[PDB]
Amino acid sequence: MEMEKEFEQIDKSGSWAAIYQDIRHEASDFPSRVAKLPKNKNRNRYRDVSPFDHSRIKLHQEDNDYINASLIKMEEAQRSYILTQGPLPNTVGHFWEMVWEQKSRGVVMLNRVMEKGSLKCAQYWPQKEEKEMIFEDTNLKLTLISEDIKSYYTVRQLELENLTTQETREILHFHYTTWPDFGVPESPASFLNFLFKVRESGSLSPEHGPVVVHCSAGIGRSGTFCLADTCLLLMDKRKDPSSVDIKKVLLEMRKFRMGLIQTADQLRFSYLAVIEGAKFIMGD
Ligand SMILES: O=C(O)c1cc(Cl)nc(Cl)c1
Image (cartoon, rainbow, N blue to C red; front, side, top):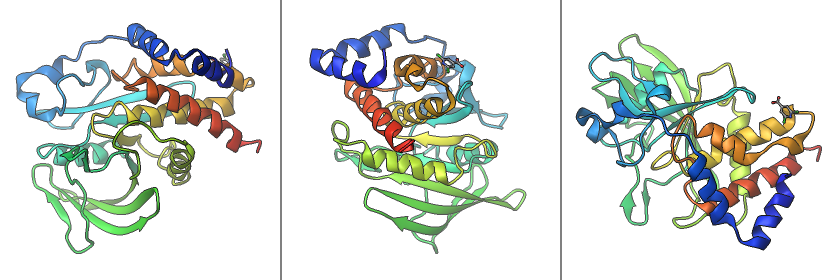
């Protein structure tokens, strides 16, 4: 079926939970043996969210190459994404090593450091220009260059230096700051505006390594971001945009990381975002 009318048909019939459970039943199951080794317990935020072995990002280190991060490679859309958990106190240096080694330009953050009164990720970037951060375990230096605070998101320019080689690179930090503590946003308008700002920066383009996107577990809000992006790109590429099947795209993405899209409300929000976004792209 088309998307917008399949949407109204699920709303009127109140079957979002049944649609979402079908996706969970059909989703791929692949081994995640490296994630579960005992030496990696303090590298995982949640015991039930692990990267598959076949798609995990490897650190370029001979001691321990493990990080809870997955490469989602979308062949028809010609987009790649790295989805990862919010960094932990003992993985902030691994996080920036990955950014460096994979040649990423941008980092997309969809959570606040504290939500619901608890810490959802480490404070992994510097908050003042004159107070840079050094990560001694991976030999990197990170400096805040500039910061632009808007009503729904903040954009930061950062400098990452490889202290071994003295090479430097500019990284863009795109921080969506207004996702609610419970539920999903009422309108997708600010999320789409944010997605378009990431696109306009070049961070999603083939001349750079894959964008790094995270929330707390790296599957829920993060899944919504890449699913909406890929679906809109396919609608631009194809002769028949109504052929884009959001449930099939989600199942394809779940071959590369488990659990993408965590609730039936997130599934409904993804439909809403793609539907509204397809109108703004055009033509009109
Ligand atoms: O390239 C394709 O796979 C494809 C598939 C569908 Cl269903 N529609 C178009 Cl236009 C292209």
